Image: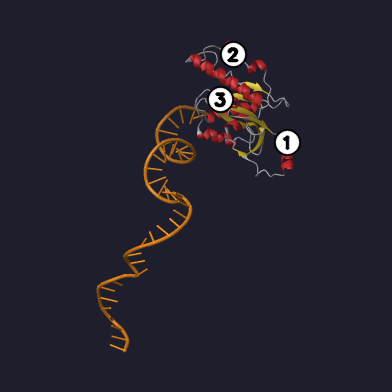
Amino acid sequence: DDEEETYRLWKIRKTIMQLCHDRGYLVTQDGLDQTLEEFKAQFGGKPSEGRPRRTDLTVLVAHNDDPTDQMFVFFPEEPKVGIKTIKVYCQRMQEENITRALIVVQQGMTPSAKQSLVDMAPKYILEQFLQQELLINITEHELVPEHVVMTKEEVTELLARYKLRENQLPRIQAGDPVARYFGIKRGQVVKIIRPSETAGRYITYRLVQ
DNA sequence: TCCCAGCTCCCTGCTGGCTCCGAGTGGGTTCTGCCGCTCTC
């Protein structure tokens, strides 16, 4: 229904705000907690043949340390995102001169488009996200523990302390849902803190490789 | 210059093939080619 799809847009915007906050970017508190009525007042009440048309939902955020990181998110119109739409989005990325973006696909993009995302990867970072994936925050589940992204100096200090190579660490795939949530890439180490039945707290390090 | 119809290419779904199947132990049995045809005494 129209009310259901309005709820869907509000919830997915809340998940985008939580993801951008967890990735280290700057979001406002009221942007973090928007109600359904407040979202409807801000963007429109009936999106079908109405005001919120999935184009005005793009978000400008910047990193806390660097105000020129300038990450956007995009909500494509068509359910099947293709090379034409991705080329339009990347050309737009070129004139506003930003490097990183998120694409929130309705159902799925074409294999040629998802390959073009890999081909465009060095200069511009493009990530595919389904609307079904972002309908809930997976980091709030009781099974999922806390994930902390480590800096390069911290990783170097860790490997010097334990006298380890990068191969000897446990691994996590780049296609992992938490890895895609944090936007981690190959070669980085994620730090997992979980409660322990026997010791109380246990810390595990995993290499994204 | 540009709009279609036709060819190209990657993913998805399905079918056929291959490997595996508890640890020890004590007895017993049958079977270890055979018909033949040239060859040798």
Residue drawn at the location 55% of the way across and 36% of the way down: A115
The residue that mark 1 highlights is A154
Q: Reply above or below: B6 against A66.
A: below
- Out of B25 and A202, give the one closest to the viewer: B25
Same-subunit check for callouts 3 and 2:
yes
User: Which circle, 1 or 3, is nearer the viewer?
Assistant: 1
Q: Is residue A207 above or below residue B36?
A: above
Name the residue located 57 percent from the left edge and 31 percent from the top edge.
Answer: A177
Whichever of labels 1 and 3 marks the residue nearer the N terminus, that label is: 3
Lateral position of residue A138 relative to residue B18, left or right: right
Q: Which amino acid does label 2 sit on?
A: Thr
* Residue that label 2 marks: A35
Q: How many labels does the image show?
A: 3
Residue under circle 3?
Answer: A134
Report helix, strand or loop for mark 1: helix
- Quarter of the image containing the C terminus of chain A? top right
Q: Where is residue A151 in the image (x, y as percent from the top left)?
A: 71, 34
Compute the Cα span from label 1 to label 2: 39 Å
Q: Are marks 1 and 2 on the same chain?
A: yes
Tell which of A132 and A189 is nearer to you: A189
Along the line of sight, the residue nearer the viewer: A115 or A93: A115
Name the residue type under label 3. Leu
